[PDB]
Length: 300
Ligand SMILES: O=C(NO)[C@@H](Cc1ccc2ccccc2c1)NS(=O)(=O)c1ccc2ccccc2c1
Ligand SMILES: O=C(NO)[C@@H](Cc1ccc2ccccc2c1)NS(=O)(=O)c1ccc2ccccc2c1
Ligand SMILES: [Zn+2]
Image 1 (spheres, rainbow, N blue to C red):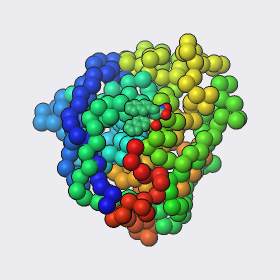
Image 2 (image 1 turned 30 degrees about the horizontal axis):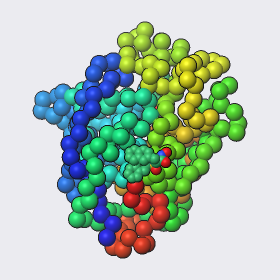
Image 3 (image 1 turned 180 degrees about the vertical axis):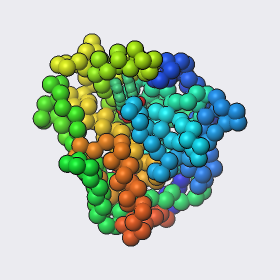
């Protein structure tokens, strides 16, 4: 039987908060079967829990967050959420003593190492997958995102960004998902933005933790980071990283084929909600024998 996963032990790391520029301590905890992914703020008293749920996500001008009934938020969950999906972590409590997840290097890779430190523990309860049964498409002008039935998990993503540092040959990326492929191909791909935008935000007291150390920073013409890009198509790899995190907000790995053209956090969430809202488009499946598990979701 394919089992749900949590962590073996509690682990802690400290990083910089993108928004405040202050040190944030992140604690990852094992959790019981079926409890899912829970983000928790422990700066607040009492602490506030935000269960990961497609309906609780909000997108801002800067990042994604989860909100509670009172619109209290926890922010910058996008890249850690992608790492959870990548390693198939079903149940976990994620604490920060601050209003935001640390930005790390702008990618998901530092979170992967932290999760490896915590270890994986298999629980005695079947892991539930969401199987796509019908085609579902959502649109935003000329932008769109789609799920189709497919016995596996594939992503095919065309980026919305247009810049001299992005050739036409580097605007699309497609992959067959797996833990190893996520780690090797996607996890290290950084977020990105304009120097003038970062300077401007910082002049307004925002994004104080923003720097070359946590993003690809471009001007109108070129990548400014002295070491350049980690991949010739790093921008679109990062957008696939984001998509993997967006889709995992339902708390289940999905068996189907994902295709997107100029999508992003908002449209990816719209697709996820559209699927879950249409009863006949999907079903929960479990695997009592490891054989019939799509290759996509094998052990790391
Ligand atoms: O080919 C690879 N990377 O480019 C393997 C090499 C590797 C790299 C980093 C590791 C870090 C910690 C433990 C083991 C590692 C192996 N990377 S990978 O295939 O993506 C991979 C990473 C981590 C794993 C942990 C446990 C089993 C298998 C793993 C494979
Ligand atoms: O990739 C992300 N989310 O998934 C980034 C997107 C983003 C949004 C706005 C930006 C403005 C200016 C520069 C870069 C930007 C990136 N959101 S984020 O990881 O929370 C983030 C936001 C702002 C940053 C500014 C500077 C460095 C890193 C940043 C990361
Ligand atoms: Zn991102």
